[PDB]
Image: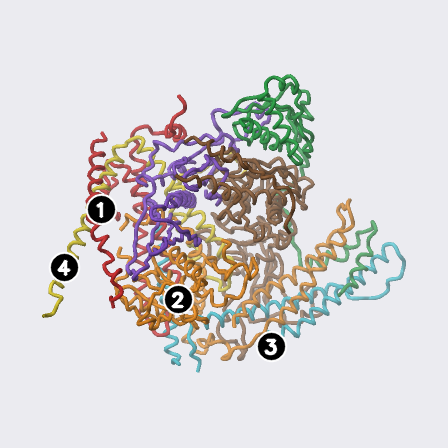
Chain colours: A purple, B green, C yellow, D orange, E cyan, F brown, G red
Amino acid sequence: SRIEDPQIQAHWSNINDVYESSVKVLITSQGYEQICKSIQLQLNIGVEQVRVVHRDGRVIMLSHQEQELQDFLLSQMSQHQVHAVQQLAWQVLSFSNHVGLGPIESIGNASAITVASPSGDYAISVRNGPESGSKIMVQFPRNQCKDLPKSDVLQDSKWSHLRGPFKEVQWNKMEGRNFVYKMELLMSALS
Amino acid sequence: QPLLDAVLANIRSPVFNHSLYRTFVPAMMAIHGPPIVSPVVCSRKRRFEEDERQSIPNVLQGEVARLDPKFLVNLDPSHCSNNGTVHLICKLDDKDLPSVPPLELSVPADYPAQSPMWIDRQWQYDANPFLQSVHRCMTSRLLQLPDKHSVTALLNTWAQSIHQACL
Amino acid sequence: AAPGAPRPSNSTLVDELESSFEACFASLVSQDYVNGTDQEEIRTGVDQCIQKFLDIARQTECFFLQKRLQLSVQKPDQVIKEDVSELRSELQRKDALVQKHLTKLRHWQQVLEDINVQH
Amino acid sequence: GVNLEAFSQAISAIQALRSSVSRVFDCLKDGMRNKETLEGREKAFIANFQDNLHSVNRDLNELERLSNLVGKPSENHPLHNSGLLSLDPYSQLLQAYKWSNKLQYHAGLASGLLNQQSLKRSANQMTTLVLPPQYVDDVISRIDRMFPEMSIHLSRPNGTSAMLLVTLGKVLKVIVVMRSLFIDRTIVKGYNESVYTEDGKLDIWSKSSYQVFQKVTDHATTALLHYQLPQMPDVVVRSFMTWLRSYIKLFQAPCQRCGKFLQDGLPPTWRDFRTLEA
Amino acid sequence: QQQQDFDPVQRYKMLIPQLKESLQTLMKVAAQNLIQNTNIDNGQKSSDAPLQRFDKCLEEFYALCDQLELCLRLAHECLSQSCDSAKHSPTLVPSLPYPQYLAVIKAQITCAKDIHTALLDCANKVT
Amino acid sequence: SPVMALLLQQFKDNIQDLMSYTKTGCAFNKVLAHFVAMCDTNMPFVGLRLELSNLEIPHQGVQVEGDGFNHAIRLLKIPPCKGISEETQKALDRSLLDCTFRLQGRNNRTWVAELVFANCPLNGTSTREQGPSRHVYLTYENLLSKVVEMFLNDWSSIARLYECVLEFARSLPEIPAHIFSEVRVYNYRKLILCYGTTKGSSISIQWNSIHQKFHIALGTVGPNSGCSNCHNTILHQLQEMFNKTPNVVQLLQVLFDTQAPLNAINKLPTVPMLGLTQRTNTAYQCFSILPQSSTHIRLAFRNMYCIDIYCRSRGVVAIRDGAYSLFDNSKLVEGFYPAPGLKTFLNMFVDSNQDA
Amino acid sequence: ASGPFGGPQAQQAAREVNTATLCRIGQETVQDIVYRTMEIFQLLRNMQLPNGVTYHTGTYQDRLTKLQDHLRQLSILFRKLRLVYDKCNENCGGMDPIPVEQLIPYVDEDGSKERREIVEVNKKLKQKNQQLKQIMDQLRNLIWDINAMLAMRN
């Protein structure tokens, strides 16, 4: 499910009862340890399906080979990692909602995650999901090349403060070894 | 409780209020004798210059300039150049069919203004059935707007109607 | 000055760290008598010094990351060699751990080869 | 007791008792500059007068004060003064007595602001996070039992891993079977439903309850999986114990009525309230 | 030499009414002087009543406020000292001999001085 | 209270199926979540409208650039403050720049507001110096989604601080000499420290809605400063002084004047009792620092003979007896014994030799 | 020049090449410096009273000494902070300005307008991971070994 995408660590129990047992599994984003914001714990069931709790007791039942919720957890972990690295290096608010606006109809079994972070005089935005535009990244400055100066040239004191144009980032072919290197583009604020 | 001082102090309401000095400033000078109260450089300058000289109160332009690049706002011949300064011409540039720009003539910043008046309504709208339906949905949604706000509500509702045109 | 546009300053990003680190210990490190009465006063200063310290730290971080990005887009061979050496070290560590586990299992089986007492 | 610190506030109180009257006469130092709107300015005077009532409040402040006096007056502080002239060049120590306190107080802020960490990485800079000695478990057990009115026991009949049980005011005992250092894979029950003393033959698992404590067990599992700090396992188990302590009452029911469900509890924010709402 | 039993509580309590009555008296004499001068400027020869000059009374009010403030500060110093002594010193007041207590105090002072010297050397090496 | 208003299936019911075909690319569940998702972020915001439907400009439902993926709620023409508005309002409007609201926290119950301003006079350096105002953040978290109250409180706070800052625009003769030091850039609270040959005497300025007065707290920043070097011992009193007038220049001048004298007077031990009492089994300290005024301090010794030394001049100070009270020999202060020996000659012996 | 002046590095050589390694080591150094600051603060936090009830002068006398070592540690880190800082400014070879503003279009997809050793190492690491997982599988499956047999296990 994930090669360049965030990998998954495995840690099973050291004492398993006759029937029941449990397994600890965390996201463990590459090259970082301050992104441990999604460590879900599940316990196996003999007759019924496994119960699982990510953070808030979200137990759900399932079948033999239907666990695609894992991808949703990966998307949420990506969002949480964006939040954490924003807290590392100018820390935007906590408006990383798990849903919103229905951007691309969000196919992929309820996969929906989108966050954003303006550090200085810029503005970053990200969105992910199950193949419904997984790598979504947008970044745009204030003083741009093309714009509408017609109604604004009349007003004096040119405003290099607001941020009008979307100017998507197209997060492809960039030097991201594990997608957790968005901090590099974040680093492009002032030097 | 100790209000005996209150009314007798309030007695000295009329204009001849100078004796208070001889009552307090000596005793004050006993405890507080500060020559340094405001020795720093200080001078009163009421005004230097004040006028917009370019448009209405800034708030409208300041807010509309923050809109998306999908909208393209400009001005017609200035028939209300100074006081009104509001008759906007907008061009929707996105993944949708283009159309005629609206009027968008607003009132003072209190904003009880359904700004668009559709100066070119009749002939520009009798052209094709599709754009006629666009106009119908536009006015139907505008009627639904409770106390519409020319600043954002107008353009947003117009864009929503233009995006609804695809049935 | 505050309202002035020009920024008349220089020589930072190196000495700044040592300066900030040493300076805000002054509440502690000081060759002066300490009045034995104070509360809710020394707090704001150390909050400010941790604030500025993490600020300049973040500044240094961003500078280092920008330098790394520039050198990578300039000299990718260096980054390639770095990744190669890292992969070599990772493979070496994996092999060492495998050998350690193998020796442990060998010892474990060898000691209890004759776990059974008699028959 | 520690009510003496309240007197400190009283200090500030009497400080105002001075400033107040000054603020009075300063207000009388000049008359109406230009009212032009109303005559509340004079009332403004009385406004300052109103603050004088605060002084009376100071006298009221003594009602809550004066709890009780401690024996052995002077609190062993001037005993050094009883020494001969040879001992007097010793006040320095007393200074350090405050200084050390400031030290702690400084750390009290510093450690606090240490909460916002900046460790961009935590690996590739080196080990054996699992505690080797089977004695630190007993240390943690004793540290937990140092807490009052909350008894803890442990037998560990399974093997190298740790197994323990804890009881509280109710019969809602909790059985925690975890690894060498950090707590994981625990469970809770109530009223001998587990009976993990000699259940069947030993401290049985039985993975069950009558659909009441199951949510609490899941929440405790979540808390264990979330409080797993990279280091300091003692801090982790202490935080776990403090979290467990928060259910000793099960009485209040804020932000809802006490009829939403079977029960209500989810305090990771150091405060319990109506469950199924966060 | 005061010999007030060194107990600040009942002293401050019994002194509060002094502040109250002194404030009352100063307000009264201020109002008297006010009505006097307001009859002087525009009235007639009516205000014939020698009252207090309002200087001595107000200043002695400040002085008693001062004395109570210094007494309260002494009380706070005493309680704070008792608190920290209890918090960071055992109870031995005639079970350890006084020379042992003095030696312990000196050892703690030396350890604090060592800590201070270490922090100073750290600050020096930093700079 | 079950309402009986229209429902109309106000959403895309039931053309939402055609919304699925509006995508660019085993279960159709993908649609269902959307609904139970969108409400989770849609219904809160309109409620905020009902709260903002009472102050001004309830322009709701705006969407920032679409790609931001966040329901946007901006602010337009912030209402005036009940405080000083006669002339400060014009400056506030001239400085009013882009500003908006976003959700926060775990997206359930938390609000965040973002503000920026025009050219900030107090904006110095060492804070990523930029022409326009970088950022102003506000966070709130209620319990029954009243945030407008705390919002307007913070607005009035920053307004009063901006008034103070605008009044600060001047040129003091010799004080600015002590490079410039105003590096504590105004975010929403102005601090200053420019004393002791470096940063030092960090002041505090803010408005807490708890009451009307301000907050003032001396600082302890500066390597070559004392152990505390603060001004706490008088700070409280000094605060009411600034309550008299917002002239920060007055605070600066008075602090620069009183620094050296209080620095000297704090050197002596005051807190410790200096062993047992000199006379009897009673308890007595050795010194008692006394902040009874703004600049006049009457240090005591063994609860008696408290001389009164203070500073009011530009470079000089004055000492006087504390038992006369503008009364040579009429009466006393009803306290400590007066006139201990002779202090005037002891002072004049080392008061001013070169002065004539 | 910039060399191994006592830096806790794993395998890095710190030579005239691999400025990437230099920048990464400097970043790691400043991160560890901040971490050491936090750590020494945490240590000095619980600086209990030297005059212990039971312990007279035994425990703390050692601990404080250890703290000194910690101090020494952070000390040399500052030295390292300089050693890298020169090197960062020393290797000014190739496109000195390097506008990141212009670079942002370059890292974008479009605007509507040597690797042999790398691949070899990649294939080697992939085969290593394959054989590693193959070795894993056995002990992974046989890991429980008591789970089904807890009915009689003790």
Alpha carbon separation for disc pair 4 and 1? 23 Å
Chain holding disc 4: C
Which residue reaches farthest bottom?
E94
Residue E56, position as x, y percentages in the image: 72, 66
Alpha carbon separation for disc pair 4 and 2? 39 Å
Q: Which residue is mark 4?
A: C107
Query: Helix, strand or loop at disc 3?
Result: loop
Pick the front one: F306 or A84 = A84
Q: Name the residue located 68 percent from the left edge and 39 percent from the top edge.
A: F87
Q: Which residue is mark 2?
A: D174
The amino acid on which the numbered mark 3 sits, given as a three-letter code, is: Gln
Pick the front one: D235 or D38 = D235
Residue B159, position as x, y percentages in the image: 56, 29
Where does the N terminus of chain B fall, quadrant-wise? bottom right
Chain holding disc 3: E
Q: Which residue is mark 1?
A: G133
Q: Is residue F329 left or right of residue C61?
A: right
